[PDB]
Image: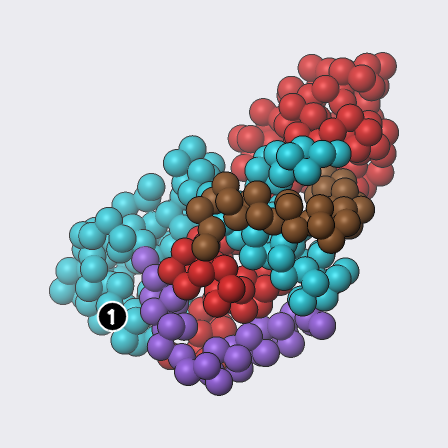
Chain colours: A purple, B red, C cyan, D brown
């Protein structure tokens, strides 16, 4: 499934990349 | 995929896919380790939830009036939502107000089933 | 309300409602203090997303085949999902498989719309 | 809205109560 494609991409990310993904999403949606 | 490429893919998911994705990360990685995606994606799903209400891909049931059977309208609300008494009477008594939303994120069909079960209680409902 | 009561209400929410509930807490409390509800609710929403699929209140698009147009079909999947090449190819190649789900949690119309575009590129699609 | 009714109920909870809401939810959905 598509989400399974996204999950596999996320778990291949380094801990710095996961953190960058997290930082960006929260940023774009105005998170504090 | 790029981080940005993954963010745009995540941004295209339905509210249900995002929920499943997260639930799937929690089971696989544990609540603690998966928490970063859980909190990072909730705003995205919240956005999708709102975009679905504005694109009419999902609807909600707004209470326009509880009529002459406030208590009977509140009954159906509790049955539907599970709210305790105080809170249910609080929501019902907000009728006529734009946020007297009994339920949202439902299908037209389900919205119709709710609108009717509410009207059968002598209330005026509006499906948005 | 009781905790058991609050919990029962949350289990009565739609995926979209839970999503919006979590997001409001995050905007209200911040990602760190809202985290607990975010992580604890995702499974609740995941369960609701699966329930919607089973009750046919939400639909998914399943690829039964891509035919001689593997490339063009992957182009549409990439268009619809934002998946990158590798990942898109992976999913498309899963055609005929139960988990060749291109998109789910969509409305019948959206599901139809998607089915159309995929069939247009040479694929055989099933809506569930 | 209904969600607002739940939120107002949640923010009234004490930290110990909130912790119990969370365990239970996670408990009922096979959380680890």
| Residue B5 in picture, x, y percent from top left | 44, 78
Give how far across and how far down residue C59 sits, in percent.
Answer: 40, 43
Q: Residues within 10 Å of mark 1 (few under 14, many from 20)?
A: some
Residue B62: x %, y % from top left: 73, 35
Tell whether A31 sits left or right of B68: left
Rendered residue at 69%/15% (across/down): B120
Q: Chain of mark 1?
A: C
**Looking at the image, which residue is at 71% across and 50% down?**
D16
- B62 or A23: which is nearer to us? A23
Is C23 rendered above or below residue A29?
above
Q: Residue at x 63, y 61 (%)?
A: C35
Q: What quarter of the picture does the N terminus of chain D occupy?
A: top right
Residue A19 falls left or right of residue B96? left
Camera-side residue of B74 and C103: B74
User: Could you say which is closer to the camera, residue D23 or residue C52?
Assistant: D23
Q: Tag count in the figure?
A: 1
Q: Residue furthest bottom?
A: A16
Q: Is residue C123 visible?
A: yes
**Taking A31 as reference, is C122 above or below it?**
above
Q: Which quadrant would residue B78 be assigned to in this image?
A: top right
Q: Which residue is mark 1?
A: C89
Q: Secondary structure at mark 1?
A: helix
Locate residue C68: give its quadrant: bottom left
Residue drawn where x is 78% and y is 37% of the image: B100
């Amino acid at each position: 499934m598509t989400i399974d494609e996204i999950i596999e991409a996320i778990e291949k990310l380094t801990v710095s990349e996961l953190a960058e993904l997290v930082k960006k999403l929260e940023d774009k949606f105005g998170v504090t | 995929m790029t981080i940005d490429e993954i963010i745009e893919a995540i941004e295209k998911l339905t509210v249900s896919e995002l929920a499943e994705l997260v639930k799937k990360l929690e089971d696989k990685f544990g609540v603690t380790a998966a928490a970063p995606v859980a909190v990072a994606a909730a705003p995205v799903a919240g956005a999708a939830a709102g975009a679905a209400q504005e694109e009419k891909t999902e609807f909600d049931v707004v209470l326009k009036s509880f009529g002459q059977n406030k208590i009977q309208v509140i009954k159906v609300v509790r049955e539907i939502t599970g709210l305790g008494l105080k809170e249910a009477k609080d929501l019902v008594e907000k009728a006529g107000s734009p946020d007297a939303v009994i339920k949202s994120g439902v299908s037209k069909e389900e919205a119709e089933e709710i609108k009717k079960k509410l009207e059968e209680a002598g209330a005026e409902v509006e499906l948005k």
